[PDB]
Image 1 (cartoon, one colour):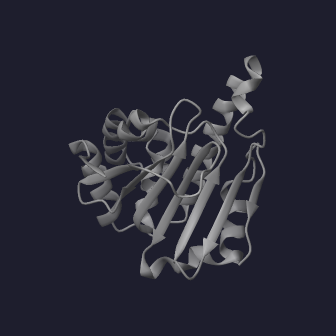
Image 2: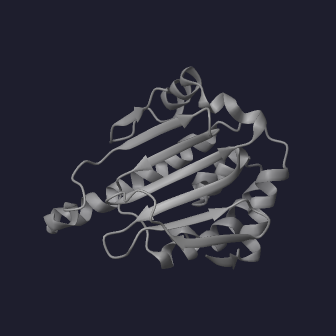
Image 3: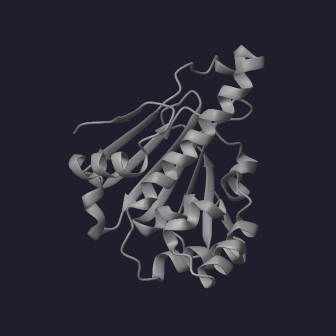
Length: 207
């Protein structure tokens, strides 16, 4: 296991997300589904000129998996995945610059639900999760697990957990008071409200 420091700007973003009073937490799901869709779009585009890119799985989709025993909500996609370098580099984002914009905007009258407009929507996971684990597999690399409970650091390790073929799995270890996001009725409602026009199937698994 390797441990890394978040850039200071990202640590500050995370703390703002964790400590700011903001009731409309449910937007985290849309943000992560949006990220999944973007990743699926990337592998799809690469496949148009090189069909072999899909040897690691031709189905392009998103699964939502709640588990009340583990208190986790997992978002899985079969998108392009991320290399180890992408993981370290803010999960393939330009987060340093996105954070600066988001903070300026929060000053010009924006609110936290607008985070995705600044390219740092992944971090909205910390509205509801105490810990986030990201398992990822890109065609050009091995399978990796990133994890962070905030506090300024994240880890990266190889994952000999179940091989995934290709894609990304975001495992949200929910805060104790956020278990509503494990209820089928609630997840269904949020998907219909904010993720109605996504171009890939979204399957909500049953417990």
